[PDB]
Length: 76
Image (cartoon, rainbow, N blue to C red; front, side, top):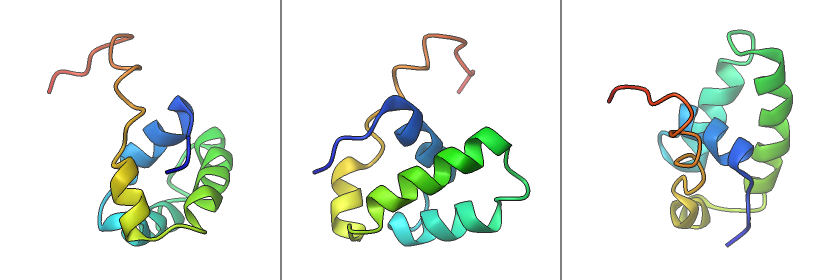
């Protein structure tokens, strides 16, 4: 298990679907629809999961996106 930051894992939380494969296909298809800062962050974080499989990304399973919820609270 690798250690990702809050910025990295929260961006993955936006497109997390179908393991890390569908996550990469979600991010790369929505790159022109994404923010510039989000896109430059995306290429760094996807390079972390590039040496990983669906198994290793399921161990991560978005761990670091709960810390930013206290800042605004999106009603869910």
